[PDB]
Length: 49
Length: 49
Length: 48
Length: 48
Image (cartoon, rainbow over all chains, first blue to last red):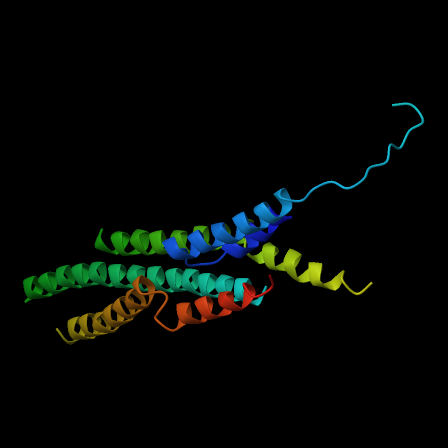
């Protein structure tokens, strides 16, 4: 979903160094937010492992 | 989505200016050959004199 | 012969118009136009 | 000779159309059109 945010954010007529840099820093913000999270609990769907 | 649609509008407009510019250049180019034919036609009228 | 030059070199202009319009037709929707469609439709799915 | 004048002075009109369209093409986006792009995109960054 963050790569879909990226593509439509960068899709425009004029691309400059600053615009693409900012689009990348927003992508990186999303990636960092989804990477720092920690697991709490889990469930195993089947009777046998 | 409105930013993207504005960008695609400006791009389609520029392509229509290629269709127009190429049409004008072709008309300019054919006029020169019309002048070449008339230059001959005038040489033949001096020769008739 | 000069009249022949007039005709064929106006034909080059007609060919450039024909192929340019065909190039706009075959690739009717580019990568940006459908991107807006997908983006606009994603907003419709938040009602539930 | 008068027919020659007709042809060349219509050609001046074709040249004015050609150069005006080229001037619109080479400078396709002015300082205002991209200003709206930057301004519109800045609104997209407030979601987080």
